[PDB]
Image (tube, coloured by chain):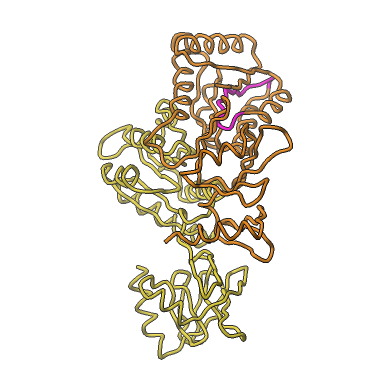
Chain colours: A orange, B yellow
Amino acid sequence: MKVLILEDVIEHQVRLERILDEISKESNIPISYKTTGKVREFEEYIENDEVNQLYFLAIDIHGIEKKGFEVAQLIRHYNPYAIIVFITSRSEFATLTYKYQVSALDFVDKDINDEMFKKRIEQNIFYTKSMLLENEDVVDYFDYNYKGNDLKIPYHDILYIETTGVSHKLRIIGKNFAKEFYGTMTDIQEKDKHTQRFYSPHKSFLVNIGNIREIDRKNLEIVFYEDHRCPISRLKIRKLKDILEKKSQ
Amino acid sequence: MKVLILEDVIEHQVRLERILDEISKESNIPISYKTTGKVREFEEYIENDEVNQLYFLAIDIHGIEKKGFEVAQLIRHYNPYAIIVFITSRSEFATLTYKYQVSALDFVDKDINDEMFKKRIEQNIFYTKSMLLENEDVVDYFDYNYKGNDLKIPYHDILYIETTGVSHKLRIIGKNFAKEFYGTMTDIQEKDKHTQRFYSPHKSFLVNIGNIREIDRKNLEIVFYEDHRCPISRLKIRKLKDILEKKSQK
């Protein structure tokens, strides 16, 4: 379980890294952390973050009050599946979270005693694991785990998956979002042989059947809901999909 | 989009519903709301029933404080990335949403003026629009097929269907667009016999029942939500259109 921490104070940096290691041994779940006080270095961290990433964000970073809210908006803007948890001594800002259009899970006051502080961040780590893990009650969600690297996003928000120049990496593209994750296109197809939620119209494209609205025969394109004529389909590959698509009833 | 509202007080239930329809016309967003006072009736629309996009909730329901949190916990249990928005008079419970591990988008106060309230409701609807993909699960679409030629476009985007010079071809008229498709006006009426979303006010026109605002008796025309009065209605057919509007939309 990869986690990201933003803290300008060395005192609270050590404190959270200590509690994280205490939980990792007690709850028997592996936790890997990356912490920085510098915004620039942490901006490169969000660039190479997990799909459902847990964030431990401060607010008053290097004399700039509400700086953490600026990076929270930035994290949410690009990743709509992030888990933003605030950790600050500026307790009065709990009201402001909503005004920043960020769907934050928790707001932890760092002035609380270590015993209750451990219990506060415990809830957030436990929520993340229990959410990502299996769950039969949850609706049709796309869960894909490739060599430790986990993913869990709804089939509704998935338009298509395309290959990348980098080995064992794929790019999931949706509405107002695009993200790179570890995995192979052959592995998803082997797991979707019965579920049948995806189709490969191109050697480098893997579309979501549920979001195919129209097919452009003349331009060799696939039109998604809200006119996303981005993936290109081959004329010979059209025959198989069209019969499968028209058999909706 | 589909929105679920939980409110026991009628005074505040109708207040939000009125504002939901007001922004629906002003920002051309189709909004279909479901309001219930009882928790058991609201839980039914979540666990045993299918999808919804936005969830507006109260906290103090039928004398039960923090009940809104308990039911919000149920929505996040079934949908971990749903959009939960709180609407309540109890301002103090704002900092308490984090205790219930509910990832709420916004906490709205009920004691604030209707000017700032409509603007705060707007923000949550504009958020849901830019987030969720406009597919079959968000709104109902006009799925038409005629001798191999297929057309699948949103119903709210259609104002009226205008006839064209070339046979077995018709044109969709929108507030910003114009799309040509193959089909017969008689074949649409034959399929929309149970659906009843299209009316024929003229031999050369087929108007969408939903986007109509007014029926001009003086100039014998049909006026839509925006100033786009182009289809023509006749006195011979105007009587059935007038009663069908008052019956369905009330």
Quadrant of residue B198 within the rendered picture: bottom left
Q: Which percent across, then down, holds residue B155?
A: 49, 66
Q: Is A211 included in the stretch rendered in magenta?
A: no
Q: Is A61 included in the stretch rendered in magenta?
A: yes
Q: Which percent across, then down, holds residue B132?
A: 53, 48
**Which quadrant is home to the C terminus of chain A?**
bottom left
Q: Which percent across, then down, holds residue A154?
A: 50, 41
Residue lying furthest bottom in this view?
Answer: B236
Q: Is residue B114 left or right of residue B165?
A: left
Q: Which percent across, then down, holds residue A198?
A: 54, 47
A193 vs B242, nearest the viewer: A193
Quadrant of residue B44 within the rendered picture: top left
A25 vs A79, nearest the viewer: A25
Q: Is residue B188 left or right of residue A148?
A: left
Q: Is residue B207 above or below residue A74?
A: below
Q: Which residue does the image show at 66% across and 32% down from the upper left?
A: A168
Q: Is residue A237 above or below residue A69?
A: below
Q: Is residue B107 above or below residue A230?
A: above
> Start and end of the magenta stretch?
A50-63
Q: Is residue A107 above or below residue A141?
A: above
B189 vs B178, nearest the viewer: B189
| Magenta portion: prevailing SS class | loop
How many marks are shown on the rendered structure?
A: 0
Q: Which residue does the image show at 45% across and 59% down from the upper left?
A: A248
Q: Which residue does the image show at 55% across and 55% down from the upper left?
A: A212
**Which quadrant is home to the N terminus of chain A?**
top right
